[PDB]
Image (cartoon, rainbow, N blue to C red):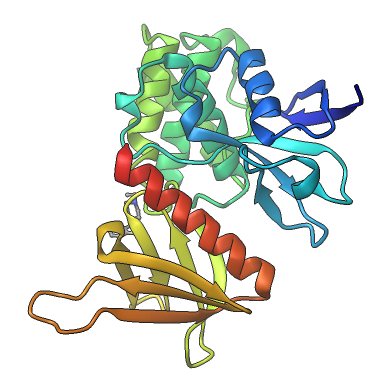
Amino acid sequence: PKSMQCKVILLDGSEYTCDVEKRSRGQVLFDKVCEHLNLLEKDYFGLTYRDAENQKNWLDPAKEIKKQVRSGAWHFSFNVKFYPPDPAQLSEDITRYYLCLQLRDDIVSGRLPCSFVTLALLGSYTVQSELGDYDPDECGSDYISEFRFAPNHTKELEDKVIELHKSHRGMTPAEAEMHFLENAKKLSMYGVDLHHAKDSEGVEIMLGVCASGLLIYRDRLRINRFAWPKVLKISYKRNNFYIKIRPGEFEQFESTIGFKLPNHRAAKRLWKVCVEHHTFFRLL
Ligand SMILES: CCN1CCC(Nc2ccccc2F)CC1
């Protein structure tokens, strides 16, 4: 019974290798990866793969792997799919640990923009979690941490991490990770999946998908936000994506709002992530 080798990049940067039957649904591989990670609160996570256009796609656990990766390698990443708006409500510390690992990559990558002071505070909690109480013996005036804290490291940032790390004496790893998450969850781009688009006039915009709803980023002064309950239908057609808005109070007609995506694949991808978010955050 023929099996395909799968390679999964984990959130710590290491590689997990396993075999699944070649006609396996995504759930088979995801279950193996979550068992490897000792992860029970699996609903927030997913696997990604790169399509023939090198775009990130979620592996649908309900569909055959072979019908998603198609002609590409069986190579995946383990990622947070649904960012909990309140990580304190998660039942296990280990779930919060994986969510911290994802957010550290979101920060270093620049997907999650962050002030100097918040970069330093987040860094200080990671250092406290992983090394424990501050020790001057490992850091003179010229200390640089092996830890990656930011898209661009400066001596000033390193110095501020150390100053805040000193303040965390006695803090345990779960406690430090919770403080990490209490800060990160407040960031304006926390858990926002961004998609390049044009408005119905051809003006370049960004669509953000998140727990609360759909964001349109237009000209810096114009951000429009559509809470999920205001959204009755998500649809795509060719390179176009549309949202059907509930009729407002005393309004006779629903309204549909339309956007242009880079290509058909990008419109279908944005539709699927919106539907998934709407379903997940309707139930959570
Ligand atoms: C603080 C983290 N997060 C930032 C994006 C914001 N998005 C949003 C707000 C209201 C309605 C629809 C929306 F998409 C939700 C909170």
